[PDB]
Length: 317
Length: 318
Image (cartoon, rainbow over all chains, first blue to last red; front, top):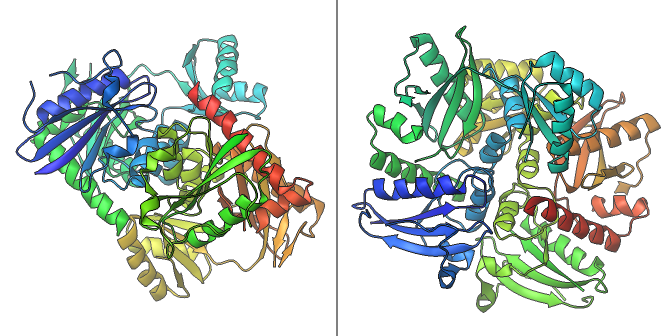
């Protein structure tokens, strides 16, 4: 009885994973409740009309090796009154707010966070600055570099604040074990972007919290990476902290819909926010974290759809 | 020789001004250099294919009273290889990164700042936090409220940090408050709009604006003053430099590209506060005039914007 538009693929490096999530989303959905229209976005950004399903498939989604050129559409022709888009797109141009902006301009409800909270959440420098300003959530140690800042003292700031190895990424990846590697990593990263992140390399436990909702934020029990332990075996104090931090991070950025909060837990029991992930994999932890809480994958989906409509009504009213 | 797609109108409250800026841009442009294709976005969000100019117009653009239904297009049909979009859209859906995202998805070069620096610049809470963390640019005194924070200590925090009157707005319902009761009433409606609410100090100070232009080579204008426009503003060299440095730093920190206008307050004892960074300023109005005083004519200003647009597009697509 509802039309879901399931966009998958994309232009980012994470685009092959996107096809996998979209395939898992399309087999997990309850068709009692949805007609599903799928559209592949190719690596060059083209929109391809591919299979509609009125009933459960069992049936491959399109890939960049299998484009059918006659099935190409005008991108705005995804549009249908009252359809809700589920953008199963990861990394840049799936999580950086460009797809969200496109769908806002097309006037369609869509699953997941809005434009501000997507771009901010994707930009670790901005995320860290917002969170250190507005919250007490600890961020993985980092240094921000804006082209123009004197290099020699940036280098010294990196060595004061961080311990080698560090990782250098343009804002929108090279490892450094010493100051020479660092200089060489920064020089290429400035060719990419005028804003550069240098981040502490961390070897610690990787523990993840699912987040769901719009105004009423729910979190899962944490689950651990390394194989998955769901739930993670951790002290109650750490469970509470991680879930509070996740919810606080989501509320502060004005996220809505879903996210997954990726934490590090050190041998001394210190918790650091590593990353807020606004469109997490569905291939993978996010669905399974909610499954452990008693929320099934098909019902998880319907909830995402109802939150999408609620944000749309709210943003259109 | 170049195709400029000029998008005007929009769904924001500033959409009537948008039409005037676009009329001013279509008249100031050098048609030696451009074929101009105009598209009106209606208040409801539809795209209307309206005039294409190959030479200077005399010649009015569409309005929400004058829509021609048959001239409606599919929004992606604005697309044309190698055409550069100038989105003359102000406020929400015009400066909030939604338009930029839509054009990025359509794969078109566009004038102005990218998705992140638009949405951040539009959100005063995030801008202020970013700038106070990464810079020494003073921000107009403010308090941020996230729905969930206990109300009483927010009220007291407003009264500790700020002096009445204050203005309350949802971050996504603007009310003035002169007292704690006005404040509570204003916050309560603002929260029906958005979970994030800004409370900002009312400031009665001199208003002085700085044009910014460029991508990696950031250029700024001499400051210009609002009340009539004094361009350049008559201010001490120390304030001029400070303003222009704060403007360029704000632009660089946010990752802006293309253009912005920075609006400052200047108080009676010579203190400077950043009020706003405006990423698509009016072209009706200070921005072109600020550059005109620097010797940069409006027509060549536009050519520079276009060339900056093609340049960011190349960096993005690579």
